[PDB]
Length: 106
Length: 99
Ligand SMILES: *[C@@H]1O[C@H](CO)[C@@H](O[C@@H]2O[C@H](CO)[C@@H](O)[C@H](O)[C@H]2NC(C)=O)[C@H](O)[C@H]1NC(C)=O
Ligand SMILES: *[C@@H]1O[C@H](CO)[C@@H](O)[C@H](O)[C@H]1NC(C)=O
Ligand SMILES: *[C@@H]1O[C@H](CO)[C@@H](O)[C@H](O)[C@H]1NC(C)=O
Ligand SMILES: *[C@@H]1O[C@H](CO)[C@@H](O)[C@H](O)[C@H]1NC(C)=O
Image (cartoon, rainbow over all chains, first blue to last red):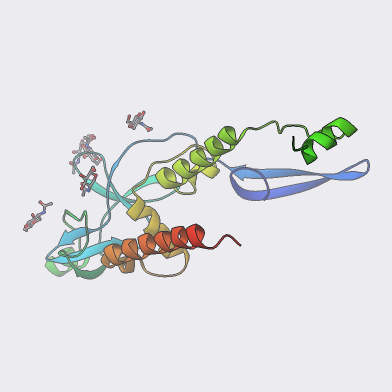
C-alpha cells in the first residue's frame, strides 16, 4: 500500500495539482541457508518456538526471529511444550536447556 | 454465404485492437506468482524470495489468524485433505455450472 517492503514511515510533500509521498520501508538484504525443524523432541515432549524458528548451522540448533538472523540457545522460556513426538512430521532430536537446574545445583 | 457481424463492423470501419500482453504472458505472470507464493510465502512480495517449507508457511498463517501452530502440526493431514477436497469441489463447480 505504501512502498515495497515493510512500511515504517511516510512524509507528505506538496506538488502542483497533487501530493507526493516519501514512503520509508524496511527491506531484507543478505540471505543465508539454514536447516530448519518444526519442533524438537526432549524427554518425550514436543517443543515449539514461541516467536521464531528452529534453525541449525550444521552442528547446533538455535531459535531466531523470522526477519533477522539472531540465534539464541533453545531453552524452556522461548519454547512451549505440546503433546509428544509421535504426531509432528519432521520433528528432530535436540536438548532444551532449563535455567532452573544450575540454580538448584548451586 | 453467411455474412458475419464482425465482417460488417470491419467493412463499416470499427476495428478491434489486440491487447499488448498475450494470454500466454498473463499465464506466465500467474504461474510466477503461484510459484513464488508456494515456495516463499509473503517474503517474495517485500524483496527477495526466501525459501521455507509449506508446513512452516501454514504455521505462520495459523499464528497470523491467532491460532497456535501446534494445531497445524497435529492436524496437518486433515488440513491437507480438506484443502484437496475444497479444490476438487471448485473443479466440480466449474465443470458443471457456467453462470
Ligand atoms: C555453529 O554455531 C556454534 C555456536 O557458535 C558453533 O559452536 C562454537 O564454535 C566456535 C567456533 O566457531 C567454537 O570456538 C566454540 O567452542 C563452539 N561452541 C560449542 C558449544 O560448540 C559451531 O562451531 C558452529 N558450527 C558450524 C559448522 O559452523
Ligand atoms: C542456498 O542453496 C541454494 C541451492 O541451490 C543456492 O542456490 C543458494 O545460493 C544458497 N544460498 C542462498 C542464500 O539461497
Ligand atoms: C521431503 O521431500 C522429499 C522429496 O519428495 C520427500 O521424499 C520427503 O518425504 C519429504 N519429507 C521429509 C520429512 O523428508
Ligand atoms: C530421537 O530419539 C528417539 C529415542 O530417544 C529415537 O527413537 C528417534 O528415532 C530419534 N529421532 C531421530 C530423528 O533420530
